[PDB]
Length: 175
Ligand SMILES: O=P(O)(O)O[C@H]1[C@H](OP(=O)(O)O)[C@@H](OP(=O)(O)O)[C@H](OP(=O)(O)O)[C@@H](OP(=O)(O)O)[C@H]1OP(=O)(O)O
Image 1 (tube, rainbow, N blue to C red):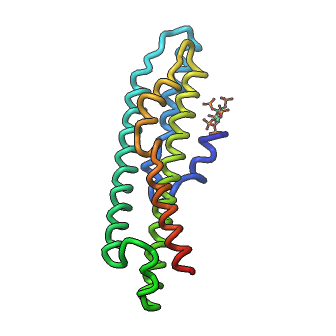
Image 2 (image 1 turned 135 degrees about the horizontal axis):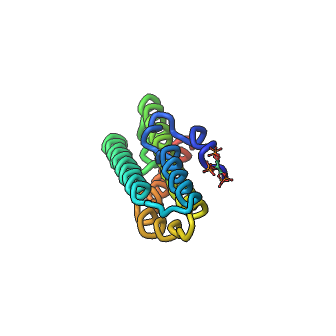
Image 3 (image 1 turned 90 degrees about the vertical axis):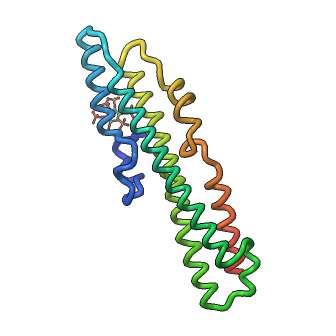
């Protein structure tokens, strides 16, 4: 899959500047590729520094949003309770307000997941690109496995877990 051309299309627009800066990372790759083309040694340290910064930022952003989503879920539990079957004790206003809150939280979680998946693709694609464009460079699988795969944005399965619950609530509430 063409990652760079599809990036705008796959970005949660409100968070655009917090995605992996694929465009800037590609210019660092191209610089290295040019040196190798000229028969010169490369210096991949500025690519990796920038890659690491991007990784820190992506993680830090995803984690903050995830902490937000959890706080939100707690506030909804405080108001409406811990299981969806409580909907039977709600009046029509309360039940509509609940539904609104649930749809918004689901939207936020879906967006968070997609942010995670697209950023992880981006790290995988940019390193693959470096490996393809620079001689005896073999970084993709090591970098992804050792630095990206341990981060919540990449490994998270809790958002999906919470999404199934929010959806179960939404269905229980519908009836
Ligand atoms: O999506 P675009 O901005 O048009 O970029 C493409 C695309 O790169 P991305 O998928 O990384 O965005 C191609 O990458 P592949 O998916 O084919 O590996 C790659 O094609 P070549 O590797 O055949 O050249 C080429 O990237 P680059 O220029 O880094 O090679 C690049 O096109 P331009 O950068 O030339 O626009």
